[PDB]
Length: 6
Image 1 (cartoon, helix red, strand yellow):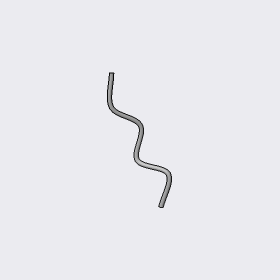
Image 2 (spheres, rainbow, N blue to C red):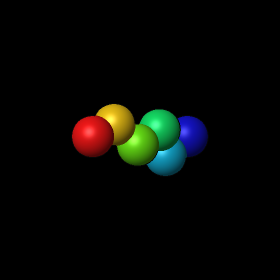
Image 3 (cartoon, rainbow, N blue to C red):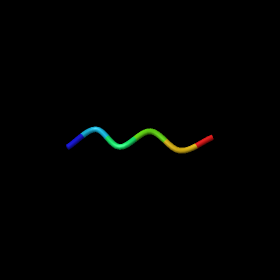
Image 4 (cartoon, rainbow, N blue to C red):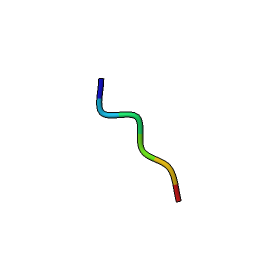
């Protein structure tokens, strides 16, 4: 569930 967010 590695939901990146930058």
